[PDB]
Image (cartoon, rainbow over all chains, first blue to last red; front, top):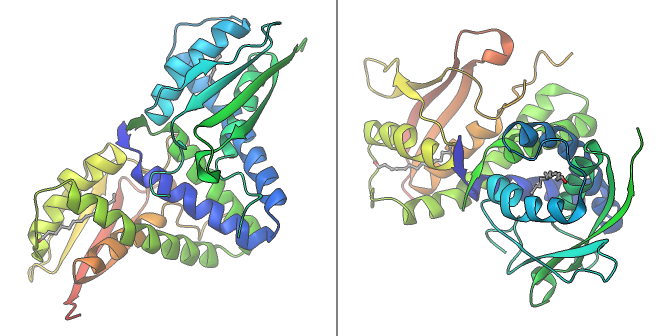
Length: 158
Length: 158
């Protein structure tokens, strides 16, 4: 089933609105969004691995290409650019020209789309890669792009 | 942007889970789902009307065809059957062979997908039709199909 993003982005809006009622502190909403993201990601990865050809890999540069060119397209209908690789090759950025989870644009500390950071961390954990994902730019805050910075921390020997 | 439904259904799952923490009474969750649905529907209708050819109409049989054959396809990637018309022509049912908002299957009173009832009522209200939508069957509860019953109440002279 392929769908337009509109019902998705409005429903995510309803969730964020509900968490703001529930917490009335934005840093708490950010954390809750990230935790729900994580629980989503750990389930999402199994759908992904069944619908892709990556097999049993744990390479970070490959992972970046797969996230950007396959997973984002499949699950959000968009393709971010991969850029800003560290010299060491252990950090990169995903750049989007707008905010994915916002189709229709006093919470300055809120990271509106923070769920996605959780999704990335949860999904990569199930393939034995401990990663940090964070928004470092957000078009919703007046930045020129939206940027998620991904840092490879370690292989998980589970 | 076209996307797979997977991230949508997992995110909706996160919302429902959050409302169950927030209310710890299922009838309250149902009502909250319906109200959020309504607020979604009132926004969704403007996207729809811009992406469709229905113009300024207020006919109930036409509305049923449009909801089932156009709107459901566009926004959820599925096409329900329209059936069980009342003799008077003021009620019909939408039949789905599973539950739309569930990709991956002590809350017996919970109407898991109740958001959709709100969406339908909110959207139709903006085109001056007062409607009731309710789940009368749910595959999640062991029924053979999922069924939303739609009743035309009145033209809204606003």
